[PDB]
Each structure stands twice: as C-alpha cells, then as structure tokens.
Image: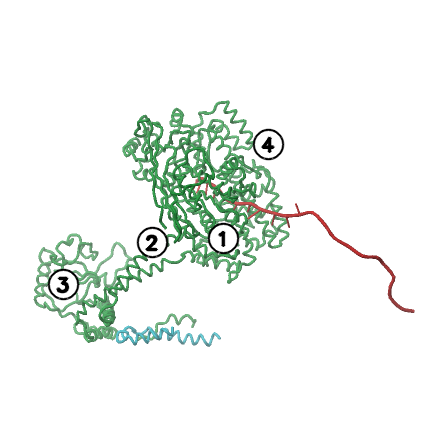
Chain colours: A green, B cyan, C red
Amino acid sequence: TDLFDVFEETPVELMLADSFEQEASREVDASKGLTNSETLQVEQDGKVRLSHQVRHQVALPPNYDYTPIAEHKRVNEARTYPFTLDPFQDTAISCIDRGESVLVSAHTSAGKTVVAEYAIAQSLKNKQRVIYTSPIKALSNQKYRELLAEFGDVGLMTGDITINPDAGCLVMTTEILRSMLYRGSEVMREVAWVIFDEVHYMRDKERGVVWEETIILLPDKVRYVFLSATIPNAMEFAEWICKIHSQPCHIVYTNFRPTPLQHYLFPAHGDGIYLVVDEKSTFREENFQKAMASISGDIYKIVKMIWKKKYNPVIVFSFSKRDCEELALKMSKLDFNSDDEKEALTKIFNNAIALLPETDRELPQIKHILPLLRRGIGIHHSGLLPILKEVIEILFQEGFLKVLFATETFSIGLNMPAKTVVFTSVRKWDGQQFRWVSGGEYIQMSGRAGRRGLDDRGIVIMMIDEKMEPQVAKGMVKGQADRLDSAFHLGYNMILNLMRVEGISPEFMLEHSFFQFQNVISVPVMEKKLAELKKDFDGIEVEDEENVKEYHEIEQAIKGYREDVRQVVTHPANALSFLQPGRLVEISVNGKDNYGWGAVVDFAKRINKRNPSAVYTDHESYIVNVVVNTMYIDSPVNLLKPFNPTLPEGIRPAEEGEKSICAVIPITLDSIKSIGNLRLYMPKDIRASGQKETVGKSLREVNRRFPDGIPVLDPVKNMKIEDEDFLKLMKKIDVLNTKLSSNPLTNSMRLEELYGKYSRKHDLHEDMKQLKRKISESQAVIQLDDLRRRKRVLRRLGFCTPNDIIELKGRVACEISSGDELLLTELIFNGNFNELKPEQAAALLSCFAFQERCKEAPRLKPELAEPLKAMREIAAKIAKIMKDSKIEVVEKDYVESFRHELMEVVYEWCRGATFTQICKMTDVYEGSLIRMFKRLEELVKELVDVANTIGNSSLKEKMEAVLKLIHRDIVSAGSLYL
Amino acid sequence: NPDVLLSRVINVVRAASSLASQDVDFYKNLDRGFSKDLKSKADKL
RNA sequence: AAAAUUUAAAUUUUUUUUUUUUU
C-alpha cells in the first residue's frame, strides 16, 4: 500500500531617414595581368573606369530633431589631411563632427582607418579620452606604433604591456573595456568617443559574447565609432543600437575596391589560366567552362612564372600549418634576395636574436627555418614563436621575403599588404567539415593583395582540384557578404559580477541582448496582421441571434457525438461474419474519402511476409475489396495495387460533374462507414472487364431500388450487438435526435446559413488568438530557461543564497576568468594543494590552461596522477548536479574537457629544465607552449588573489613559490614593434 | 501533521479520481448549468 | 584541422620642571 498507488487504480466507472545611395566612379590604369589580353574594356586615355557605391542612412530615436548630415558644413578639419578624401569618408567625418555615432562597414583596404584618425583629435582638442579597440595584440601593435608615431600621447593597454596609463588617447583590447566596465574605471569618466574596429566578431561563436555585452554596458552619453567588414545586414545593428543607448546612429555602406582584383583558375596539373572574374566583377562562364575544359609541386611552375611575371610578393594559403612546411620544402631550390640583402637580412636578423639569451640563441626550430628565411621565403602560422611571428612580417613588410606560406591569422593580420594570393586548398575545415569555403570568408580572404599607391592591380590565383559546380565557384568567388548575427550564450563569471555589482541585473543584459532580435523584427508585421485580424473579426462578430452560438454549442455537441460512435461502428472484432460478397456496404475510407454505397468483392487479411514484427490494426490487417460506382474516371486504376490499401493520389471519387466509373479498392474495417442488409449478384468472375461495372449499374439499380436509403445493418436488429456499453453509448446521439429537432429555429430563419454566418465569425474567433498565442509565445527572453537552470547551479554549489546573495564561495572566482571558475573554487575548497608542492600543483594547473587535444602522454608519476585522479573526482559530482540541473552536458565529455598531458613537461620546467630539452617531449609547437605558459602566469597571478580573500597563509607562501619557478628565461618574451 | 491531512488528501485524491470517471459531457449537452456547476466546482479548484 | 582571447594597486612635523600616601 505505497502511497502513490492511488494514482494507479482504475476508478469506479459506470527609424529610417536620410536613406540614400550615392555613386562614385573613377578610372584605373590599364593592366593585362598574366592573360595577354587586357582585363577590361579600355578607355580613350588608356584608363579603365570603375564605379562603386556610397550608401548612407541613419537610425532614429523617436521625436528626435534631425537635420541632414549631407548638409553638414564642417567648420574645421579637426584633423586635416594631405590628399583628396573620399565622399563616404567625407560623409563619415561629418557624423563625428556633428556628434552622433555611426557604423561604417567597408573593406580594410578602403580607408576605414582614416575615419578613426579624425575622431582622435576632436576628442583631443576637447581634451576627451578615446578608446580604440582591437581583438588582437598585434592588431594594436600595428596601430599603436603607428599612432605613437602619429600623435605620440597615446596610452596602450594590453595583457602583455601597458604604456602610459594616463595618456589622452587609449588603445586597448575588447575585454579590458569589459573588465574596466565591471569594476568601473574612472578612466571611463573622461571618454566620449569609442572606436570599435572589427565589429563583426560578435558572430564569433567563441568570443563574440564579449563584444556584444560590453556595448550593452555602455553609458548612453558616449559617442561611438564602428568599423568592420561589409555585411549586407548592417542596418539591423544600427536598428539594434539606436534604441538600447537611445541616440541616433548613421550607417555608411560601400563596396569599394581600392586596388583592382583579378581572379584566376589553375587546375592542379591543368594548364589553363583563366580570368573568370574581372575587375568589373563579372562571372566569365566560358573561361570557367574553359577551366572546366582545362581540368584533365605544381606551384613550382607557377611561382617562377609569377617571378617572371614579377608579381612579388606572393602569399600561399594552406588549410593547415604542417602543409606549409611541406610546401616550403616543395619550393626551396630557388632564392630571392641579393647577398647584400641577405647580409641585410642576416645582420638585422641577429638583432632579433639579440634580445634572447645566448643559450636561447641556438634553439633548434629557428636554426632550421632561417635558410628558408634566407631564401627570400617566409611561412606564417601560429606555432612559431611570437618573436618569430613578428620578424617575418617585418621582412614581409620590407619585402625581403617574397613568399609567404600562410593561414588565417595573416588573413586577419593586416597592415602587411600583398600583391599575389594563392589558394592551395579550395575547401577548408570549419570545425565540422572540410567544406567549400563560403562567400564573405573568401571576401575577407580576398583583398589582401594589392598595395594602394604601388601595386597596379590585385592578383587572385586559386588552385582547384575538382570540376566545381558553377554556382559554387560563384558562391565562393563571386561571393556574398556573410550575415552577422549574435552568438550570445552564457558564462558564469558574467553571472557572478552582475550579482556582485549591485546596480543592474543579468536579466537586464538579456533585455538588450541582440540574440533576441530574431524575436524582435517580424512580430510588428504580425501585430499589423493582428491589427488586421482584430478588425475583420469585429465585422462578423455579432450575428442576429445568440442561440446560433448555442446552436453551434449544440453543433459542437453534435459533431463529437457522431465522431465517437463511428470508431465504435468501425469495431475491430466486428464488421465480421457479415463481409460476404454482394452485401451492400457504405464506403468511407478512414473518415477522409467517402465513396458512397458499394458491394463487397470479398474479405481477406493482409499478410506481412517482408516484415514479421510490424503492426497492422485489427481493422487494417483485414483487407476487404468492394466495387463502388463512385470511382472517378481518371483515377489511376492501373496504379493501385490489389489487396493493398496504400492508395496513391489522383485516386478519388468523381467530383462535381466528373465521370463516375467502377473500380475495386482494397479496404479495411476503418473504411466501413456502414453496412446495409441486401445482397445482389456479386460475380464469382473476379476481373473480366465488366463484372465490376455490372455491380455499379446494379448499385444504380439498387440506387433505383432504395433511392432514399438502404436499411443499414442495425447493431440492435441485424448484427444483434447487445452491449450495455454499446447501447447506452448511443444515448448521447439520442439527445441530439431529440434536442436538435426540438430547438427553435433548428433550420428556420436560414439558421443553416446563419450557422456559417456564426461560423465565419467563429473562425475569426479562433484564428486571431491562435495567431495571438504565437505572438505572445513570440515575446519573452527564451534564454531564461538556460539562466534559470544556472540559478540552480550556484545555489547547489552554495555560491549564493536562494535569495541570490553571493557567498564567499562565489566571491572567490570574481577574480577568475582565465579558467573553469566552476571547478577552481571547489579544488581550493577541497584544499588538496596543502600537500602539493609547487612542482606538483603546477601540473594540475596545466590541466586547465590548454584545450586542444594531441598525442597521449604516458601515465605519469602518480603524485601528479593521483591529484589528477583527485580533481577528476570533484568535477563529476559537480557535473552530476549539472546533469541534475537539466543542463544537457555529457558528464563523460565534461571530463575530457580537461586535458592532462603536458603535466610532465610542466613538471620539469618547474625543475629548471631546458627549453631545448622539453621541445623533445611534444609535437605541440613552441609558441603554443608559451601560449599556455603566458596563460599560466595569468592563472597563478589570479590564484594569488584567492588566499588574500581567504587567509590561507600557507597557500600564499606556496603560490608565489610557483610563480618564481615559472616566470623566467624564455617566459620573458617581448615584442619588437613596441 | 502528515498522517491526518494527507489521509484527507487521499480522501480527496480518490474523490478526484472519482470525478471524471463518469461520462461528463452528456449533461454538459443537457444543460450549460451542469457544465457551469462543473465550472463552478472548478472555481473551487 | 586552423584561428585567436584577457589587469589597474597610496609620499615631505602643533605645546606647559621633578613631592608627597599608616613599625
């Protein structure tokens, strides 16, 4: 008698303005490229005219006082400029000068730089501070030393290096703003202008959360700049921003081409070299189809030809780092520097090696690459050292290295222009698939060739190894600007500090998150449709009588009571021992296609021999065949299969005026609408072209015999079905037999028509709110269900009260962002480092600071592994309750989120090991080691914070003891631009 | 007290199990006031 | 298979003498 069994028993049962596109067109010096014909139609000067677009519009607050920015006579060049600026740049600087924020979205070679140059001085002449943003240190390192040469009084802020903290102008990466927006730097309090570059990284599924949220955390007084690659859907951003910080924002689109591009196709081992996209951006079908014709290592022909073409510099693009090193070796019999230049190479090169220790001046990987680097040849990828990464690009920017073997950083790594771009792998792996690269990928991966004042053109050469579909090479090369949408997700350190800072809420973040702008846009259209539907409803809304609703309420009771009986009329262990041939039966298959009255051909059962375990209904395993004369003349009589009720389409009754014929259909007990009590001549002659048609004329003679109605087999009088279940069931209709006829104006006063008068009101009664449920369903923050689960988590972790008041537990990771904050609190709260040594626990910190999988390390010395076994025990119970949290995380896969393999190398660098020696213990490249090494310092320094907040004095003794033992010789790397 | 008031809950649990066991739509046909009383008994609910 | 991601801790001068506590 367990107390849930009572659930189990069966009971006792009886805005848009200033919207204009402008045109700009100039002439370009002629060039043939490597096609011997000219690339375009020549003009009379020997010039070639191009043209391009200048769109402008501005997003509007309600009721705002607007005057056109095209009229804005700029009273002063707050920065003057030597040459003729461009019309959109002219359009740009007025928006700064008149004092409203603006997105301009162009390509990097266009001169978006120049607009950023202007607002500095207008901030500086008004003594204001200004933020210049970047996602990359080396993006800033470009812009810093540039602006440091330009205006000098510029602060740089980096996780690596701050310079001049109280300068007037500030250049810093994205998260630092976010970090100094959480704790409220007063640095912010003299800033009125922000230069957001690289705005499109909001669609980063990795990091784009930071760009989005940090803009939401802006005070609304501030003016802003926005620079990014061309997207088609730029206005959506302005349409998002202009509300949520409540000031106007202009847009400027262009598609401008600075130096003119020429797309070529090299079939690998094919010999056609085909301009298929001109500078006027036209798909050549025929050259492509010649390139389809010319599709029947290879680079080594191409390069010396390009060197004969003198199209230096030239950049090679792989889709993986190791491929370049191979492609480095496939080319290296050449040389492209003079020994004067190679002295100019080597001497300056040693000054790059001068900032290392002499023990470090002999490190192996750099010994290997340097003769390739001597040969006028460079390689680009991350895996090098950062000191290697900078020296190459210099010598690339100073042109000693004609060749670059590159990946996707240098695609983003600008201020290092090219002349020639090589596409070695057409496709590329996207985390899920070695896929045909999409459009704006390739468009971003286009423009890097062609120096502005120097290069005549842009040389685009793609090696292909498949006869690609025509629209794909279009969709790759004649490309599309890719859509920019929010990749907003959640993260717990964000969830911390919004409770920690009092003034706002995490919910408030979601109210202004762009991730629901999907849920924003189409709804007022549907409101407009609802504002339509709320009107059309009101027309039919009142009929002449209320009782027609009650009649429909009678008809609602009518329609269901016939419904329940027919499924009891179609009884599975009935309509049996009466299915004999000639028994006149009413045919209505499944309640979908009523076929009049017919005569039984036979009855049978469908035998499933191909699938033994499947299920037919006890209705549907039984196969009846019945001749009806209610078959349409043009039904596929030849296509329905005998003894199979799988009827194809076109098979139907003869509709209004359509010719009725006779045919035989395989039917079941579900098809039986009713069965009469007469048997005519059913032919034992099965199919002889005119025995089923004698049935239907005899059916018509039976439709002469009872034109009014066949006496159906009564379950009372004919099938003799006598169940108190069955007989009392009909009583629901035996009110409708009475009460429908009883009701005043059952059909008087055109009540049948007045029903449809009510019904056309009643449908409008249904479908608005049906739509309005959808719109009300289209309201809310859909992310709350994630968030409401995460509200569980910290309470389960005790990081806050159920009143959400943050505990000291949750207070810990407030200075932790650099790792799993969810774990790192518990490890220290499990205190397992009390008997870890600085060499020992550091290997446990290698279990955090690195993500990418590689070869198996051995099972190491167990005094590492048992703490590694110990921390593994902790996070499972954590992820257990995460599984309990309805948070869809595979606990197993949550564990292998932790990577435990470099621990040995970490254990030995703690013991003073040589950089040379530890290089042997992995394949993982040396900068990537440092990329977790200098990550690891950021960890340990944020670990020093914790014992200050707790008082674990042993820990603080142990913490900087670690920090002594990592921060040393090669970890002391600095850069050259700075 | 658990054993008292839940025994009264069990009492109404079975009564809740006793509710829609009969065919209820038939007198909803025979009057709105059956249904409206059933609505009114749901107004308790 | 690439790509990359984070910090910030406080400075320079105004004051009045000591006895004296129950064999």
Residue A716 visible at all: yes
Residue holding disc 1 = A494
**Total numbered circles:** 4
Co-location on one chain, circles 4 and 1: yes
Q: Amino acid at mark 4?
A: Glu
Q: Are marks 2 and 3 in contact (CB under 8 Å)?
A: no
Q: Chain of mark 2?
A: A
From the viewer's perspective, is the residue at label 2 or at label 3 nearer? 2
Q: Earlier in the sequence, mark 2 or mark 3?
A: 2
> Is residue A825 rendered to the left or right of residue A615?
right
Q: Which residue, given by chain and number where applicable, does mark 4 sit on?
A: A358
Front one among C12 and A352: C12
Residue picked out by circle 2: A522
The reply to whether label 3 and label 4 mark residues of one chain is yes
Kind of element beneath mark 3: strand
Q: How far is mark 4 from mark 1, CA to CA?
A: 45 Å
**Whole-percent x and y of residue A956?**
62, 50
Residue farthest to the top? A339
Query: Closest to the observer: A694 or A577?
Result: A694
The 10 Å Cα crowd at callout 2, few under 14, some 14 to 19, many 20 or more, is few
Res B8 → quadrant: bottom left
Among the two numbered marks 3 and 1 on one chain, the one whose residue lies closer to the N terminus: 1
Q: Dot 4: within a 10 Å radius of its alpha carbon, few (fewer than 14), some, or many (20 or more) residues? A: few
